[PDB]
Amino acid sequence: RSRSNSGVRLDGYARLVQQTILCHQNPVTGLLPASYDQKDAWVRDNVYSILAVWGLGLAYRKNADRDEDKAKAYELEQSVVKLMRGL
Amino acid sequence: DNETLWDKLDHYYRIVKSTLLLYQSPTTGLFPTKTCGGDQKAKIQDSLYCAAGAWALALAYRRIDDDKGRTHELEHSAIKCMRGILYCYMRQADKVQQFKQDPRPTTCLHSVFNVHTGDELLSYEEYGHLQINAVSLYLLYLVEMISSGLQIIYNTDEVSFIQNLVFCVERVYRVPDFGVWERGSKYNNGSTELHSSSVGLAKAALEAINGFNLFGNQGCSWSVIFVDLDAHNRNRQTLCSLLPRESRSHNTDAALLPCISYPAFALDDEVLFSQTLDKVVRKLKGKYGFKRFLRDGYRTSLEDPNRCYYKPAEIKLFDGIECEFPIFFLYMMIDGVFRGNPKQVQEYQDLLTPVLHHTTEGYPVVPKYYYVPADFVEYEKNNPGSQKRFPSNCGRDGKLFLWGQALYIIAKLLADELISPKDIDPVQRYVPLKDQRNVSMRFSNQGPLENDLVVHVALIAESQRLQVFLNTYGIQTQTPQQVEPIQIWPQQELVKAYLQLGINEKLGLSGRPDRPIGCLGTSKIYRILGKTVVCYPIIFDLSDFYMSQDVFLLIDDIKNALQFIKQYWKMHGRPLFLVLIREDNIRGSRFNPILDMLAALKKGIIGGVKVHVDRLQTLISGAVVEQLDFLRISDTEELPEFKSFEELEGQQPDVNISEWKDKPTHEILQKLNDCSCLASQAILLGILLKREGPNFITKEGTVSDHIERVYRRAGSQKLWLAVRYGAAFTQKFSSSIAPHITTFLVHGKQVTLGAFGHEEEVISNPLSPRVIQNIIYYKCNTHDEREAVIQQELVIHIGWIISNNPELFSGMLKIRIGWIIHAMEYELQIRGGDKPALDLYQLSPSEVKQLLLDILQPQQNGRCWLNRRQIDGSLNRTPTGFYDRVWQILERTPNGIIVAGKHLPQQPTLSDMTMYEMNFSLLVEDTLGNIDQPQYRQIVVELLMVVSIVLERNPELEFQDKVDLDRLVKEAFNEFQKDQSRLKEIEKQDDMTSFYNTPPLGKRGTCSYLTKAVMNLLLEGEVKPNNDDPCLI
């Protein structure tokens, strides 16, 4: 009924990824700048920086029996695809 | 027609409110069967259709915005009835639990309830409550109304009960029931019998309810109903096998329209649909209605009302005077609207109008049945359909047929296009010829005619030593550890996981019964407890039986499983077929057959089934995952991790059976140490469990497990004697034998389980694994325990053939196991020459299948004709349509047929049954059963064929006296002697050999003398001048 405790702690990780990485993803291209000062997208860093989104998306997909769990897993998974399509 | 749609709907509102809704029970919501009389009876089948009628008018009133509260009244009149059935059903939850574990007529849900209280009204003795049509229709309509927006299920506790109702419906393929007509058959013996309508309704109920959220739009993952595909598949295999016949007794039934048309639409093949529709239209349509079935005596003038059961001879008097039910004009009317044929709608509307009656207010009354009066029965029989029939229900009497009245509303609303066909069919039970992409309903992505299904085949090796060593031969495989986060399970672990589905400690429901998951179920990808689990097919389990250890059968089991998935997988995703290879399969000469199959899978095709060999991670990425959420909603997140598959890190018997069994001394225990053979051990341990108790201690340990160790160890060597004794003396019984038998008799084939010349038990009706286990070991075989193991060997083997090569057993109406094992054992004598022949218990189960296949062939090539008549005779194989020709024979022999002291008279044989009927086909073999020589059987079966040839092409001749075929066989016999004595003067006297070896067709063949024998006695009779070809002279 209620969401699994793993998903609840993933929301803490979802906040961690969103506040750090996914909030910097370019809406148009899916790329990720290195920082504020460095506004370009390095191929290596973008691939590496998207792993947390990839791992979290896999973790969310692992227990995606509910619409929001499907949707946040889908968003994370296709945020990785956006990045790699952009790259 | 300027009438407003309010006035059109108000017209039906009055009928609905005054004819069926007026009688809805305020307490239970059920609709009484008898409106006048004070009877408390409320039938689920009738009440369900009454709910649909109010629901149908609610759907019509959904098009009126100013409904004046009539949509709510009619929507919630259906909900009140639907919940009342649930209230009655849940009050019988102890029966639902029992019917899940052991489906039986005495453990089933009641189909008749008190309309005012919901209590149990009639016991199993008074009433036949086993009516799967009721439970299936409840599940079907429950999906229909919930999909339309009616909120019937209120909490997960009810969801658990509906899941248990689904479990009761899964097993129905093997459960004979009394059917919709609460009668079973024409004979009224109170005998349950498998009905196409009941099994088809179960198929319709399972398709609509699979993955269905009982909460509607206000629903989450914990209200979806899970359906076992394979029990649904075996329900459909039963439906396709039984059809176009309703059952064994009924070639057709009016109940087929509720099954193959509204509300079920259970047939997905348009050829069969047509075939099955015509037999209803031809043999049951009438002016006043449809006859429920041929020779139906329900409420007929020739029926004794006091007696609840019909005499075996009473069904004869019921021909031509069967009650005609107007309700099936409506069913055809609903069929016409659904199928887009307006001529059908108008034609059956023009037939209802004469049979419709009206109340004092002009409201239509649909009579239950139209019966010929007692004064007009005999005129009706001579010329059917020419005499007036009186209505059962006329209106203005107080007696109303609520099922007919409700179904009138549905058909008329459809006919006047006030409700769309899709409105009463929100979950689409009727699908047009655009038959693609419906789960569980035969409409895959490819559609209705193309079936080039690609099965995802994952190659799994049990150990790395096998993994790398197979890799050295060009085959890529992955050990379970290589596929790590994924879990490869035995199908049992899936059953153990499924044990928690549908449990209600409040209702005392125990969950899904412990039944093996078959190929289609294991073809799905499951996610349990956050772990993605793929179960390999049961065919790879080394516990159920020992033919999985035979590499050739495993290769054929792998092939036929893929063909089984290619034929019966109809879900959105691609099925996953995990292939498990054990070291036993590679060791020895078994590599060469296993490698070619694996190479074929790598090549992409095997058995004509397209397969895709790839890593398990590849074949799992985008497939639909069955979420076993019930294992987490109960907060059982700490449930024990189900045991996934764990990677692993020569002479003939010198001891004869009679040599030491006769030996009275107990020194045989020392002889056990003296001898060195495994079979000698496998016999010595067996007597020790009988002579010295069940769990005596031996050198290795207890007797019970020491024989189990030997059985496990003997199979490793492939010493088949010891593995056959090992499985026989432990009373081993795989889960497949019982369903295999059920597959046999739904094809029209009786099964006998016993050795030749000993007690044989005929399996007329489907039986549970428990009784068949008692059948196959305790009563049937006691001369030799290995008889049962060999008996179970063929049953799976015939189960293998009956599906791949169904034509192979055509004519063989009775699959008699021991009679078949004679055919192989006698064939070994034939092939053995003047040498000690092979033993059927020495042959590997592959050679058992091949020799069985050899001795079954349509025509053995070039063999001794004597021997052919032996192979065909032992199998009791008959020509196609042979049983039909016996009618044409019996139709034209007034005094019948006498053979081997068994007489088949013209009467009451012709009067009692029909000449497509299955019962007559059983009657001939009972008459034919006294012939001991299988070769002598064929020459008689040959003779009955030729006399049928004489009778058909020569209708002028007719027999006077009893046709004693032994004399005709004997008469044609001596003519062969005197002819051959003239040739070479063979000195053998009363020897069939020369007569048997000659081919029928030839210069002087058997059927030539058989033809002469018939004509000599056929010309001994008066010739009848025939008007078909008036004799020119």
Image (spheres, coloured by chain):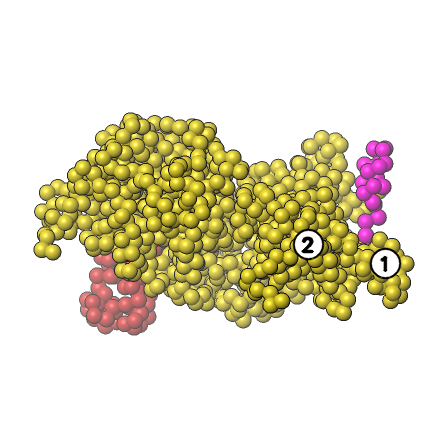
Judging from the image, what is the letter of the chain drawn in red? A
Q: Residue at x 10, y 52 (%)?
A: B4
Indicate the position of residue B641 as horizontal and vertical percent values: 46, 44
- What secondary structure is found at the residue carrying circle 1? loop
Of discs 1 and 2, which sits in the foreground? 2
Magenta residues? B652-673
Chain label for disc 2: B
Q: Are the residues under marks 1 and 2 on the same chain? A: yes
Rendered yellow, the chain in question is: B
Q: Decide which of tag 1 and tag 2 comes sooner along the chain.
A: 1
The amino acid pointed to by label 1 is: Asp
Kindly identify the residue that appears in the image at 85 percent across and 33 percent down: B664
- Viewer-nearest residue: B1015 or B661: B1015
Find residue B853 and report its image quarter.
Answer: bottom right
State the residue at coordinates (11%, 48%): B7
Q: Under tag 2, what secondary structure?
A: loop
Q: Amino acid at mark 2?
A: Gly
**Mark 1 Cα shell of 10 Å, populated few (<14), some (14-19), many (≥20):** few
| Residue that mark 1 sits on | B834
Q: Quadrant of the C terminus of chain B?
A: bottom right
Q: Tell me if residue B261 can be seen.
A: yes
Residue B826 occupies quadrant? bottom right
Q: Is residue B497 visible?
A: no
Question: How many callouts does the rendering have?
Answer: 2
| Chain at numbered mark 1 | B
Residue identified by numbered label 2: B1021
> Is residue B665 shown in magenta?
yes
Of residues B260 and B658, which is closer to you in this image?
Answer: B260
- Image location of residue B386, percent across then percent down: 37, 48
Residue shown at 34% from the left, 27% from the top: B119
Reply above or below: B475 against B824.
below
Query: Eyeballing the image, is B865 above or below B644?
Result: below
